[PDB]
Image (tube, rainbow over all chains, first blue to last red; front, side, top):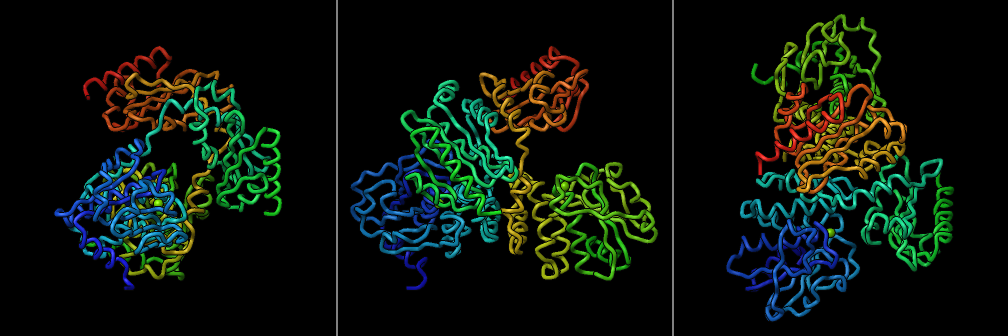
Length: 316
Length: 316
Ligand SMILES: [Mg+2]
Ligand SMILES: [Mg+2]
């Protein structure tokens, strides 16, 4: 065929039970897109058995709970790996133990795992692809407040509340359409934006210990083992406050290094400049806009700063 | 008539020069709605003279600059007080010195100043009303990247990036339509989200000095004159960090009190509970969700806390 959506819905109508998967570390989209496809199907073919397997992140518990698959249901069922770049990165690994495999994602097509592959690279999120799918079957009536909830939240998180560049006029329109359904976005949004007061004091530290260039283009934060225990926080926890300096006016590149003990795992992100470049120089790597390195000392951490800062000289 | 939009466009076509106004303390909407109506008109009747008067807030300088009216142009011209609850709160006061007055706003109609009054109470923002207006004249083609810019930014700020409850599915749709025009929202958005690193250290203090109830429902911050000079910041500046604790999980009501010297001007905001109530008890007042009081001591500040906290006992 040429209209993959139809071939999917077909494979679906011909299976009494289908289970959906998503990548490992879950995000609002990976959550909404999964629970969404599910909630949708369950509304269209109540005679079938739709399940969503996953580790279940308590962080997204409010979006919806997952299902406990008995691994023997994979016998004669259709597996749908929703939102997942590469297969190994799929959550439950018994997905390949189904009748046929079908994947829906919005990341660059490099794996193409699964029989039928539909990747709308230009989509803001998989949730969005799901809305497109159900919208292609005029089921915008069969859907309700429960389904739209996840789909919204999904698009919301994957685009940071329609802020990121991946937000298109269509994305808005879809968001527009979901809000039609009664569910109160303001509420849902807040419960998603909640924060732990426990970590707030530390975050204040980050704000009190900067490191901006005279030009404001470069900014760093050294989290010494001392502060890690002074504020009583694990190296992991503190490492989530990277973008706590991103909003500084004029900031072009910033690095956040927290000492784990025998190495200083530093996460480096830039406004929009090839950075993973220098990352490799130090044995690191990653996306050109958000890479990571694991120096063995602050003296080396500084060499990284010097290398990063020099990158700003080529641009002006 | 019954279709105010037409009566406006009429009064417009019959005036070689029209000037637009907005309320005093400007906001992104009041800015976008003004510059927007203007930029629009200037595209429709280049033969006329459209001007936008205002004090000009350097904060919104990037949205667009205002015009310097010679007060004698008001001779035979149409004045359009865009986005402004009450007349006294209008910026340039020589507005009443025009041929006829016409106002467009989205706040409750309590003033009704001006000949023709159009208030879409259910609109997310005046900018949105402007899009509606131009959209009613099929001028979505005459408009360009420059006009949509302000209108977007306007809706954006007035709804905090489609987060507030005033965000409707139509609001999204309008946002959707504006993005069609080439202007890059991501960029524009950031320049609007920029922050001053100068105040960041202090903000860290606020995060390091909370005051949450055992239930997390109540939170306060006492900004003593000491810290006001320890971090070298004016009482005004520090007072803008009220909602710096709003995202705490479970927070229902919070107060932020900063000592100005001979009085402690405290701004009190709640999640969604009638609060201006207690405000009056202390000689204050304001909206039920964001009021203000000016106690003469921290001992009194505490009485306010007690009164506010007791308000949480009636609800559960
Ligand atoms: Mg995704
Ligand atoms: Mg407004």
